[PDB]
Length: 104
Image (cartoon, rainbow, N blue to C red):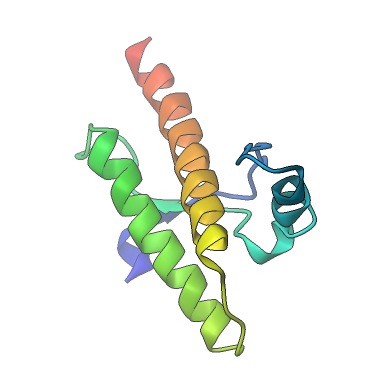
């Protein structure tokens, strides 16, 4: 269905904290297990951030999980937490960038 969407070219990874130094590696070493892009629609027709991010996270984390399970990989509950937060941060980033270029 992502023909009816947009996909961002490769993004920054933020360095999200979680609460253990163990998790600093469980994120940082593991970055390649989480997406480097996010799927969306632009601010055209869909000027909100809330359901924009929540649906970007739905679409992207679903699609990325399928793309994992079709390769017989899996994700821990912590992996979903990271994924969700990175994916939200990357979506927020893109939307804030295009929103600012609209707010001008």
